[PDB]
Length: 58
Length: 289
Length: 79
View 1: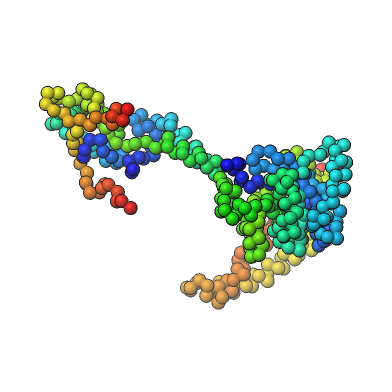
View 2: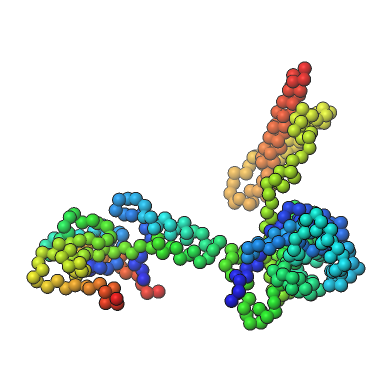
């Protein structure tokens, strides 16, 4: 399942970001839909981003 | 451009209804008429305060029979008592016909629109006032112009949509091609409600008044005898009536006009009464002496 | 667009969403006044996990594990 995609409340239980990946939550997963701040292991190597759209239109 | 134009709920006072029924009932079957006096507030709240009747004309409802000499002079008697308020429409009674507006009635209503364009035409049907029903309906002209350009939806905006659709054919055709029919609600104060509600001086005294005793004797005898005759039917019924196919069981053993139930209702009504009967006699004796 | 649900309540604490109460009492009265329909909007909440990289404040692309039968929650048809 991709990041920033429709997640019904039922599939939200099972959601578990790969531990081996760079992105590991700073605390135990919130487990409920919402902004969950993630720690990125490496800023050197590329992190492809989705820049927020409001700033372009503004 | 203008108002919402939702047809008014005609809020009919307790007095105006009481007079209207009385007025029509006296005149039946000869058509009766009068003007409605009221006051116009909100967008759709017309409070019909009171009505008075105009002297029966041999032309029935007519523009001719709206007699300005009578009308004016009446305004003036009511003026001195300070009960005068603007004319907000007119009512008349057709008993001969259902509730709708005849071609003659449409002209009559057209004159009223000049006073107030939210004026109502109220049809009272006093022949069917003999039922528990009060058969009354209220109408307000629609312009032909509205229907030709198909602009009619304006008038039926933002509403619960409950419309009376009783009475069709010619009547309904006329209604759709001339007026708009909308609900009537009855608003009354609790002061008014209580006065009416109150009954006799002897009403709160009646429980020590009691039936003549020759009739209690008669009644006791009648009930014992009657149940016996229905009990025959009931014994016959449960001889059999344990097969199959529901409706057939009811025809075979006379399970239609069902004996068990009709017996259970009579037995209990008489039983409750007989408790009341004794209760009064003992109390009367002891309280007084 | 098939991404919103009506929540009864905040799902974190287990205790009422202020907005959501106002929406539904306002929605339920529309017979009296039809324009108030719109108030069901305050009850509408988007449901979606949005992961936010705390070292840039932007949305990282990455993939998460969901142990579930994948076909059983397939996206809706187009009617």
